[PDB]
Amino acid sequence: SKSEMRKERINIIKNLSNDITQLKQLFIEKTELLDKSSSDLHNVVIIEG
Amino acid sequence: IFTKEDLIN
């Protein structure tokens, strides 16, 4: 029991870490994509002449 | 740092 209970603890903690991994990967990815669009926006500007 | 829109210009 308790051996496999601990293994399935590890499994559900692994699932939770997969959820955190989804959070990190996709949100940092789309955030850096927003930053790419920001350099398209905030860093492609015309003012002077 | 350096950007590609530099190279676009």
Image (tube, coloured by chain):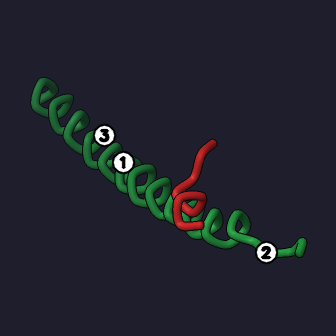
Chain B appears what colour? Answer: red
Marks 1/2 same chain: yes
SS type, badge 3: helix
Residue A4, horizontal then vertical, whole percent: 10, 31
Q: Nearer the viewer, mark 3 or mark 2?
A: 2
Q: In this view, does A38 lie to the left or right of B4?
A: right
Residue A21, horizontal then vertical, whole percent: 36, 48
Picture quadrant where residue A48 is located: bottom right
- Does A22 appear above or below A2? below
Query: Is disc 3 in contact with disc 2, using a CB cutoff of under 8 Å?
Result: no
Label disc, if present, on residue A21 of the rendered structure: 1
- Does A3 appear above or below A9? above
Identified by mark 2, the residue type is Ile
SS type, badge 2: loop
For disc 2, the marked residue is A46
Q: Which chain carries label 2?
A: A
SS type, badge 1: helix
Nearest the eye: A18 or A42: A42
Identified by mark 1, the residue type is Thr
Nearest the eye: A4 or B5: B5
Q: Which of marks 1 and 2 is in front?
A: 2
Q: How far apart are marks 3 and 2 (CA)?
A: 51 Å
